[PDB]
Image (cartoon, rainbow over all chains, first blue to last red; front, side, top):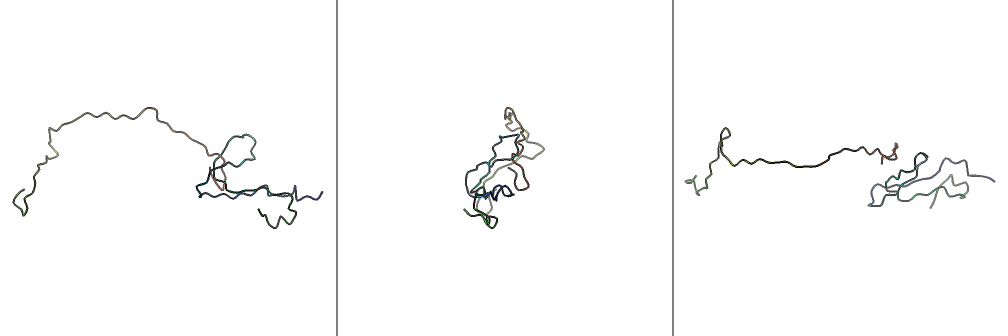
Length: 63
Length: 51
């Protein structure tokens, strides 16, 4: 298979901006109990690692 | 009052110790009804941001 993979510590990345008048969307937690609980802070752009961009993807992310 | 340059207009004012008569009125203050305080614990706390 060759995986890059299960290995990675990167699970997302997230640009946030506390200025632009914007609208506030919630980010998900990893908590289980509970879900709930919608939070509200502006969230601009944000992506998961795109499989597969093949290493090097360790070198750089791009969107 | 009068008798300085231009003539001025005059009022007398009572001392403090005695007015004594002035038109006093009982006043009722009214703000109601239930006053409260809530503690919204921050959702999603972190070292980077509280929300």
